[PDB]
Image (spheres, rainbow, N blue to C red):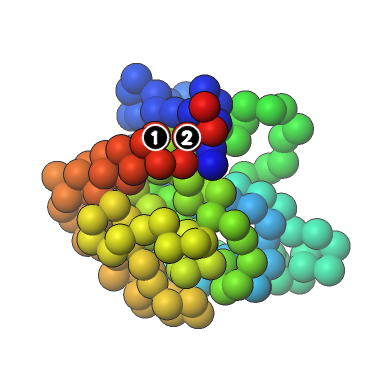
Amino acid sequence: GVDTQVFYPAENRQQQWQDKKIPGKYGIGIFGRIRKTKGTQEFIEAAIVTLKKYPDWTAVVIGEATPRDLDFKKELEQKVKQAGLDKQIIFIGFIADSNEIPSWYRALDIVVCASHKEGFGLPALEAMASKCAVIATKAGAWPEIIVDDENGYLVEPKSSQQIADKLDMLISDSKLRYKIAQNGYDLVTTKYKIQ
Protein backbone atom coordinates (compact mmCIF):
# COMPACT_ATOMS: atom_id res chain seq x y z
CA GLY A 1 0.00 0.00 0.00
CA VAL A 2 0.81 3.66 -0.16
CA ASP A 3 0.75 6.44 2.48
CA THR A 4 -1.86 8.86 1.16
CA GLN A 5 -0.75 11.49 3.75
CA VAL A 6 2.60 11.60 1.85
CA PHE A 7 1.51 10.88 -1.73
CA TYR A 8 -1.48 12.99 -2.76
CA PRO A 9 -2.47 15.47 -5.54
CA ALA A 10 -1.53 19.13 -5.46
CA GLU A 11 -4.22 21.75 -5.60
CA ASN A 12 -2.75 23.05 -8.90
CA ARG A 13 -0.56 20.74 -10.99
CA GLN A 14 0.37 23.41 -13.55
CA GLN A 15 1.70 25.60 -10.73
CA GLN A 16 3.60 22.70 -9.08
CA TRP A 17 5.29 22.05 -12.43
CA GLN A 18 6.12 25.77 -12.85
CA ASP A 19 7.75 25.78 -9.39
CA LYS A 20 10.30 23.18 -10.60
CA LYS A 21 11.82 25.82 -12.93
CA ILE A 22 12.28 23.50 -15.88
CA PRO A 23 11.23 24.01 -19.47
CA GLY A 24 7.74 23.18 -20.72
CA LYS A 25 4.25 23.28 -19.32
CA TYR A 26 3.39 19.59 -18.64
CA GLY A 27 5.54 16.77 -17.39
CA ILE A 28 6.11 13.06 -17.80
CA GLY A 29 8.35 11.26 -15.32
CA ILE A 30 10.15 8.03 -14.59
CA PHE A 31 11.34 7.31 -11.04
CA GLY A 32 14.14 5.24 -9.67
CA ARG A 33 17.53 3.99 -10.52
CA ILE A 34 18.83 4.61 -14.05
CA ARG A 35 19.65 1.12 -15.33
CA LYS A 36 18.71 -0.83 -18.43
CA THR A 37 16.68 -3.42 -16.49
CA LYS A 38 14.55 -0.54 -15.11
CA GLY A 39 13.48 0.37 -18.66
CA THR A 40 15.06 3.79 -18.65
CA GLN A 41 16.10 3.30 -22.28
CA GLU A 42 12.58 2.47 -23.47
CA PHE A 43 11.44 5.59 -21.64
CA ILE A 44 14.03 7.83 -23.28
CA GLU A 45 13.42 6.33 -26.73
CA ALA A 46 9.64 6.77 -26.26
CA ALA A 47 10.15 10.36 -25.13
CA ILE A 48 12.31 11.11 -28.17
CA VAL A 49 9.54 9.89 -30.51
CA THR A 50 6.74 11.56 -28.56
CA LEU A 51 8.15 14.91 -27.63
CA LYS A 52 9.12 15.90 -31.16
CA LYS A 53 5.36 16.04 -31.65
CA TYR A 54 4.47 17.97 -28.45
CA PRO A 55 6.63 21.01 -27.71
CA ASP A 56 4.87 21.93 -24.44
CA TRP A 57 5.67 18.55 -22.85
CA THR A 58 8.83 17.60 -21.00
CA ALA A 59 10.11 14.26 -19.73
CA VAL A 60 12.09 14.01 -16.49
CA VAL A 61 14.19 11.16 -15.21
CA ILE A 62 14.03 11.25 -11.38
CA GLY A 63 16.86 9.06 -10.04
CA GLU A 64 20.52 8.34 -10.58
CA ALA A 65 22.83 5.86 -12.12
CA THR A 66 25.15 3.93 -9.79
CA PRO A 67 28.81 3.74 -10.89
CA ARG A 68 28.34 0.60 -12.96
CA ASP A 69 25.65 2.37 -15.00
CA LEU A 70 27.22 5.81 -15.52
CA ASP A 71 28.10 4.78 -19.10
CA PHE A 72 24.44 3.90 -19.72
CA LYS A 73 23.27 7.27 -18.46
CA LYS A 74 25.82 9.01 -20.73
CA GLU A 75 24.50 7.08 -23.75
CA LEU A 76 20.95 8.14 -22.90
CA GLU A 77 22.06 11.80 -22.62
CA GLN A 78 23.73 11.46 -26.03
CA LYS A 79 20.60 10.02 -27.61
CA VAL A 80 18.64 13.04 -26.37
CA LYS A 81 21.26 15.54 -27.58
CA GLN A 82 21.54 13.89 -31.00
CA ALA A 83 17.72 14.04 -31.34
CA GLY A 84 17.84 17.80 -30.57
CA LEU A 85 15.65 17.31 -27.47
CA ASP A 86 17.80 18.48 -24.55
CA LYS A 87 15.15 21.16 -23.79
CA GLN A 88 12.47 18.51 -23.37
CA ILE A 89 14.22 15.48 -21.77
CA ILE A 90 15.92 16.33 -18.45
CA PHE A 91 17.86 14.17 -15.96
CA ILE A 92 17.14 15.59 -12.51
CA GLY A 93 19.92 15.77 -9.92
CA PHE A 94 19.80 13.77 -6.67
CA ILE A 95 18.45 15.46 -3.52
CA ALA A 96 18.32 13.84 -0.06
CA ASP A 97 15.20 15.70 1.13
CA SER A 98 12.22 13.50 2.13
CA ASN A 99 9.52 15.29 0.12
CA GLU A 100 11.35 16.04 -3.11
CA ILE A 101 10.02 12.80 -4.53
CA PRO A 102 6.34 13.20 -3.43
CA SER A 103 6.52 16.77 -4.77
CA TRP A 104 7.63 15.45 -8.16
CA TYR A 105 4.59 13.22 -8.46
CA ARG A 106 2.50 16.32 -7.72
CA ALA A 107 4.11 18.15 -10.64
CA LEU A 108 3.63 15.38 -13.25
CA ASP A 109 0.70 14.56 -15.52
CA ILE A 110 2.00 11.13 -16.57
CA VAL A 111 4.30 8.61 -14.90
CA VAL A 112 5.94 5.70 -16.69
CA CYS A 113 6.93 2.55 -14.79
CA ALA A 114 9.00 0.70 -17.41
CA SER A 115 10.80 -1.94 -15.34
CA HIS A 116 11.45 -5.22 -17.07
CA LYS A 117 11.13 -7.40 -13.94
CA GLU A 118 12.01 -5.63 -10.70
CA GLY A 119 9.47 -3.90 -8.48
CA PHE A 120 6.56 -4.23 -6.16
CA GLY A 121 4.37 -1.63 -7.91
CA LEU A 122 5.01 1.08 -5.33
CA PRO A 123 5.87 3.87 -7.78
CA ALA A 124 2.69 3.04 -9.79
CA LEU A 125 0.73 3.29 -6.52
CA GLU A 126 2.53 6.51 -5.51
CA ALA A 127 1.78 8.00 -8.94
CA MET A 128 -1.88 6.94 -8.83
CA ALA A 129 -2.29 8.29 -5.30
CA SER A 130 -1.04 11.59 -6.70
CA LYS A 131 -3.53 11.47 -9.58
CA CYS A 132 -0.85 10.97 -12.24
CA ALA A 133 -1.89 8.88 -15.27
CA VAL A 134 0.28 5.73 -15.27
CA ILE A 135 1.76 3.72 -18.10
CA ALA A 136 3.39 0.55 -16.79
CA THR A 137 4.81 -2.83 -17.61
CA LYS A 138 3.58 -5.93 -15.68
CA ALA A 139 6.54 -5.40 -13.29
CA GLY A 140 5.90 -1.66 -13.03
CA ALA A 141 2.39 -2.25 -11.72
CA TRP A 142 2.93 -5.52 -9.79
CA PRO A 143 0.73 -7.38 -8.92
CA GLU A 144 -1.95 -6.62 -11.55
CA ILE A 145 -2.87 -3.17 -10.16
CA ILE A 146 -3.86 -1.70 -13.53
CA VAL A 147 -6.79 -2.46 -15.81
CA ASP A 148 -5.68 -1.24 -19.23
CA ASP A 149 -7.65 1.79 -20.51
CA GLU A 150 -9.57 2.04 -17.22
CA ASN A 151 -7.10 3.13 -14.53
CA GLY A 152 -3.82 3.18 -16.41
CA TYR A 153 -2.11 1.50 -19.32
CA LEU A 154 -0.14 -1.63 -19.66
CA VAL A 155 2.73 -2.12 -22.08
CA GLU A 156 5.05 -4.97 -22.80
CA PRO A 157 8.56 -4.63 -21.39
CA LYS A 158 11.35 -3.65 -23.79
CA SER A 159 8.97 -1.76 -26.15
CA SER A 160 9.65 1.91 -26.50
CA GLN A 161 7.06 2.37 -29.27
CA GLN A 162 4.28 0.92 -27.09
CA ILE A 163 5.14 3.51 -24.40
CA ALA A 164 5.18 6.27 -27.03
CA ASP A 165 1.78 5.25 -28.35
CA LYS A 166 0.32 5.54 -24.85
CA LEU A 167 2.00 8.87 -24.19
CA ASP A 168 0.73 10.19 -27.57
CA MET A 169 -2.85 9.13 -26.65
CA LEU A 170 -2.79 10.60 -23.13
CA ILE A 171 -1.29 13.89 -24.28
CA SER A 172 -3.66 14.23 -27.22
CA ASP A 173 -6.84 13.42 -25.28
CA SER A 174 -6.70 15.31 -22.02
CA LYS A 175 -10.24 14.38 -21.03
CA LEU A 176 -9.31 10.71 -21.29
CA ARG A 177 -6.06 11.32 -19.40
CA TYR A 178 -7.85 12.99 -16.52
CA LYS A 179 -10.43 10.21 -16.32
CA ILE A 180 -7.77 7.47 -16.33
CA ALA A 181 -5.85 9.35 -13.63
CA GLN A 182 -8.93 9.86 -11.47
CA ASN A 183 -9.88 6.20 -11.82
CA GLY A 184 -6.36 5.17 -10.69
CA TYR A 185 -6.62 7.54 -7.74
CA ASP A 186 -10.05 6.14 -6.78
CA LEU A 187 -8.70 2.61 -6.88
CA VAL A 188 -5.60 3.18 -4.80
CA THR A 189 -7.24 5.38 -2.14
CA THR A 190 -9.88 2.64 -1.70
CA LYS A 191 -7.91 -0.59 -2.03
CA TYR A 192 -4.22 0.22 -1.43
CA LYS A 193 -4.38 2.92 1.29
CA ILE A 194 -2.16 2.07 4.33
CA GLN A 195 -4.54 3.86 6.74
SS at mark 1 in the image: helix
Q: Can you tell which mark lies on residue 189?
A: 1
The answer to which of 171 and 121 lies nearer the viewer is: 121
Name the amino acid, label 1.
Answer: Thr
Residue name at image x 71 percent, y 27 percent = 97
Classed neighbour count for the residue bearing mark 1: other residues with Cα under 10 Å, few (<14), some (14–19), many (≥20) = many
Q: Are marks 1 and 2 in contact (CB under 8 Å)?
A: yes
Residue 14 place in picture, x, y as percent: 33, 29
Determine the residue positioned at 43% across, 63% down: 144
Percent x, y for residue 82?
52, 71
Regarding residue 107, the answer to whether it shows in the image is no
Whether residue 147 sits left or right of residue 159 in the image: it is: left
172 vs 28, left or right, is: left
* Tally of marks: 2
Q: Is residue 70 left or right of residue 44?
A: right
| Circle 2 crowding by C-alpha within 10 Å: few under 14, some 14–19, many from 20 | some
Name the residue nearer the viewer: 176 or 182. 182
Residue 88's place in the image compared with 3, above or below, is below
Q: Secondary structure at mark 2?
A: loop
Residue placed at 38% from the left, 72% from the top?
A: 155
Q: Nearer the viewer, residue 121 or 190?
A: 190
The quadrant of the rendering that contains the N terminus is top right
Q: Provide the residue designation for mark 2.
A: 193
Asked which quadrant contains residue 70, the reply is: bottom right
- Expressed as whole percent of the image width and height from the top left, the position of residue 185 reads 34, 39
Residue furthest out toward the top: 11
Q: Amino acid at mark 2?
A: Lys
Cα distance between the residues tagged 1 and 2: 5 Å
Of residues 187 and 155, the one drawn nearer to the viewer in this rendering = 187
How far across and down, in percent of the image, does residue 151 sit? 29, 52
